[PDB]
Length: 262
Ligand SMILES: CCCCCCCC/C=C\CCCCCCCC(=O)OC[C@H](O)CO
Ligand SMILES: CCCCCCCC/C=C\CCCCCCCC(=O)OC[C@H](O)CO
Ligand SMILES: *C/C=C(C)/C=C/C=C(C)/C=C/C1=C(C)CCCC1(C)C
Ligand SMILES: CCCCCCCC/C=C\CCCCCCCC(=O)O
Ligand SMILES: CCCCCCCC/C=C\CCCCCCCC(=O)O
Ligand SMILES: [Br-]
Ligand SMILES: [Br-]
Ligand SMILES: [Br-]
Ligand SMILES: [Br-]
Ligand SMILES: [Br-]
Image 1: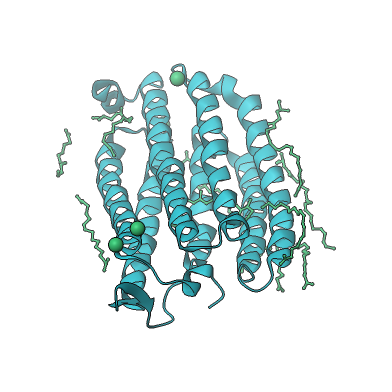
Image 2: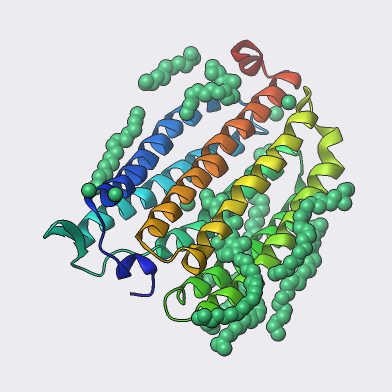
């Protein structure tokens, strides 16, 4: 009842488009899961955790998207020409809770292919995860107010954005100070990964703000469309680039299975 999805009836076209976005998301992540599983054998031990983390992200995101899809069809029934709310079973909050797990995985696989190790890896991962969790938690509290108190959504969103900015500064600083350690030409690739991240992750706060500028049923559809673009870009496309970097550095480091695969 705290999310705008509960306020509207949906046309068949709107309802089925949202359902198809979510189900397509499930298929894309589980298809990618198999790809990451099969190619892990071509990654040197030093980097193989990075590809395993992509497997974990795929199933984590795939399970939440599948949960959202079933919750969506549980919550609404087609009555008198529109889909109308029947049960309080759908909310976006499950995405936020899941981010607590998937964002640390996405960040860790970046740090691994940057060749960080030992105390710097543990220290950098700790500050990044704390910053990320602060961002997620404040965002989560903010969206509890997207119906009742838009001013509170904005203020919690400003606090969240402060964590986001600091997180991105840590990430960017480590990338630009360590890309010279990267093998096989991937010092060039990692810069593109950073820009892909900036683009894809910024779509989430845009989705967060939809209630402020498009509080209607088409805004609900737009938000799910933005989440879909962002999810595929931040998890699947990002994971493919991380895996490419891992295999390329593995080969440059003399790992034979990587050399043959390329
Ligand atoms: C009264 C309400 C409370 C107000 C306060 C809440 C807002 C504070 C937010 C950010 C400050 C913390 C930023 C400090 C981060 C420094 C540590 C760090 O980033 O280390 C990175 C390094 O590159 C890795 O080794
Ligand atoms: C809540 C409202 C507050 C609004 C606040 C607006 C300030 C935005 C500024 C920067 C965004 C952070 C982007 C981080 C980009 C990476 C920066 C970086 O990596 O620095 C390069 C390094 O110094 C080379 O060695
Ligand atoms: C796969 C999911 C990912 C990469 C989720 C990323 C989420 C964010 C970057 C969220 C950022 C937010 C803000 C910067 C302010 C508004 C609240 C959030 C949590 C949506
Ligand atoms: C309060 C929350 C703090 C969370 C901190 C999490 C710390 C995680 C630290 C690094 C995990 C990396 C483990 C795998 C190392 C891979 C390196 C390698 O095998 O080449
Ligand atoms: C996620 C990015 C957050 C950006 C910070 C928000 C910037 C705030 C800008 C002006 C706030 C104006 C407050 C007006 C409250 C409207 C109350 C209402 O109409 O219900
Ligand atoms: Br229709
Ligand atoms: Br329509
Ligand atoms: Br190795
Ligand atoms: Br997720
Ligand atoms: Br490149």
